[PDB]
Amino acid sequence: KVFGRCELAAAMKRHGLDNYRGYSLGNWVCAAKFESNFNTQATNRNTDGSTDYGILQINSRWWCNDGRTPGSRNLCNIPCSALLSSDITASVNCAKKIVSDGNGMNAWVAWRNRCKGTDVQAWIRGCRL
Ligand SMILES: [Au+]
Ligand SMILES: [Cl-]
Ligand SMILES: [Cl-]
Ligand SMILES: [Cl-]
Ligand code: NA
């Protein structure tokens, strides 16, 4: 599923991501945008063999289990395939855990290089929230 910009914002808020750990909704969306371009089915392989899944490109090294990432963890306790679902609940609960891990949203390289310090608010401009 490819979400609409305003559509994902709504979903993200309903699931309490809006301002979770102090990160405004617009930050979360800017992330989704650059991590997956709003497509719940996005997968991207990393050189180290781990794999990024979902709207937030959650990694198999620590957060989910794909059964193919030698010596990794599954800290969110979920098959990485739950992160490719049309319902974003799982991605959202795993992100809450990820973002609370000490480094905040830097955990998402794309957010740091493309969202951090930008007018993230633009991402929700217009949305009926
Ligand atoms: Au949802
Ligand atoms: Cl594994
Ligand atoms: Cl949803
Ligand atoms: Cl922080
Ligand atoms: Na795993």
Image: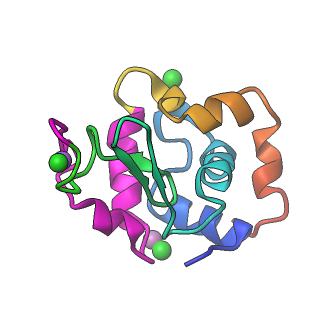
Which residue is at a point 38% across and 49% down the rendered structure image? 51
Which residue is at a point 63% across and 36% down the rendered structure image? 111
Considering only vertical position in the picture, is 9 above or below 120? Answer: below
- Taking depth in this image into account, of 4 and 20 the one nearest to the observer is 4
Where in the figure is residue 35, as x and y percent of width and height? 59, 50
Considering only vertical position in the picture, is 62 above or below 40? Answer: above
Instruction: Look at the image and give the residue range highlighted in magenta.
Output: 70-99
Quarter of image, res 110: top right
Please tell me how many numbered marks the rendered image carries: 0
- Taking depth in this image into account, of 70 and 38 the one nearest to the observer is 70
- Left or right of residue 89, residue 119 in this image: right
Q: Is residue 76 something one can see in this rendering?
A: yes
Which residue is at a point 43% across and 67% down the rendered structure image? 88
Where in the figure is residue 50, as x and y percent of width and height? 33, 43
- Left or right of residue 40, residue 84 in this image: left
Where in the figure is residue 113, as x and y percent of width and height? 69, 29
How are the residues colored? rainbow
Quarter of image, res 103: top left
Q: Does residue 38 belong to the magenta stretch? A: no
